[PDB]
Length: 138
Ligand SMILES: [Ca+2]
Ligand SMILES: [Ca+2]
Ligand SMILES: [Ca+2]
Ligand SMILES: [Ca+2]
Image (cartoon, rainbow, N blue to C red; front, side, top):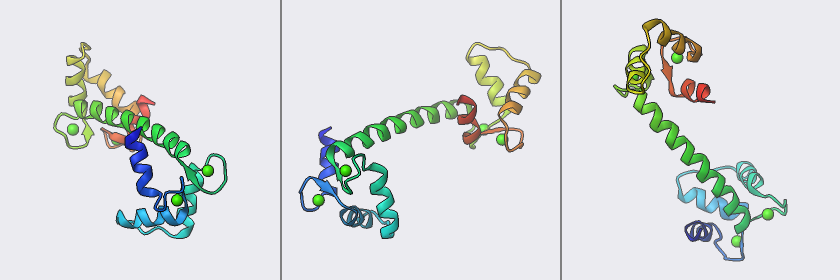
């Protein structure tokens, strides 16, 4: 929380308790991004729960708690995908899947693992990439 309040303190350049689009802009610029006023206003609006035009700590903390929880769940889905992607090439092959499933207690045939890939293989390249992996978890 204090880590999140500490982050808040860097955005609030003048310490009045709120983050304006200009203050957000100043930070983003120090991060190697130079968004247009248009973009900056979208970013504020996305977080500005009471609509008053600026972001306060409770608004900031609330978005960060979701972003943390979203980030935690992606890190963990990413962990699972690597486990399946044995050679690490970013695609899960029929053979890696079959092999990892046997490790998961499920001795499957080439036909069964082939159907499992096809059900997941949106782009049709005979394998499962990370995007397709997340969809069939979903
Ligand atoms: Ca301020
Ligand atoms: Ca607000
Ligand atoms: Ca692979
Ligand atoms: Ca595919």
